[PDB]
Every structure is written in structure tokens, then in C-alpha cells.
Image (cartoon, rainbow over all chains, first blue to last red; front, top):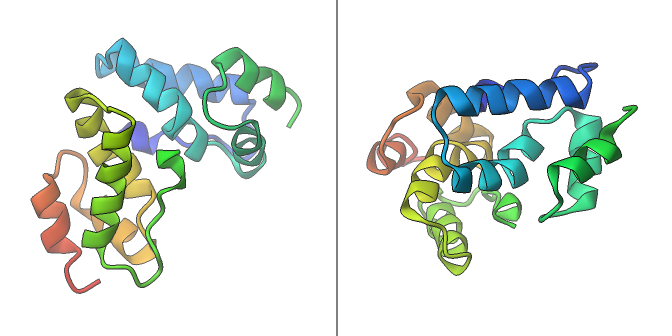
Length: 73
Length: 73
């Protein structure tokens, strides 16, 4: 179901992040689960441009870092 | 890093499952984390045939059900 949150081809990364975590909240994801989801699913469910940027940034990036790198495209 | 465990094009689902969980163990994934990982990453990192089958099975399938459906390939 969080598996169904994929980023739109032109959706700003930031709006994709609200839906992702919004969906995680509804399912009462624990804090530990949000941390693992941030580094995995949030990345793989991003659009091809953000996906490439996030993979390039690498594991253990913070959300803020993820967002700075994906402002624009 | 579990992000980089993807299923080989001809690899049997089952062998992909041992690597997935093996990788999860090394990273000391909690039980709650394994359960979420089973339903998300295990599915998205499956090869195109398995991926289709697992999505068709849907959220909340057990691993055993995931495996029975992906026997054959």
C-alpha cells in the first residue's frame, strides 16, 4: 500500500514526500520503520530523475539532504 | 544497501529470499522491520515475473504464500 505511493513524472519530490509519510502515518508506522522506509522505499518509488539523484546520494542521507538534492528535477 | 539486493533475471525467488533476509540480518533489522520489508522491498526488488506475481498476490501475503506463487519462476 505504501508500495502504491509512487512519485508522479513531474510531481515535485516534496509533494511525493508528504504522500509517502502521510500514508505511513495512516498505517501507524513506527519510528524505526519510517527510518528504514526513508532509505529504501522512498527511494525506489521516486520518479526516474529523483531516483537517480537519491541513489547517487546513497544510504544514510537525511530527508533534508534528499530534498535539497531533488529541488528542481 | 538492501536497496541493492535485486533478484537475478533467472535466479529462483527462493535464492533471492535468502540474500534479502541475509542482508537484513547483517543490518540487525528488527522483527517489525522484516515484516514491513517482506511486503515492500522484497516485492519491488523481485525480477519482472516475480514482481508481477507478488503484486498480484497483494499486501499481507505471507512469505510462504509469496514462495508458492513464485515457484516455477
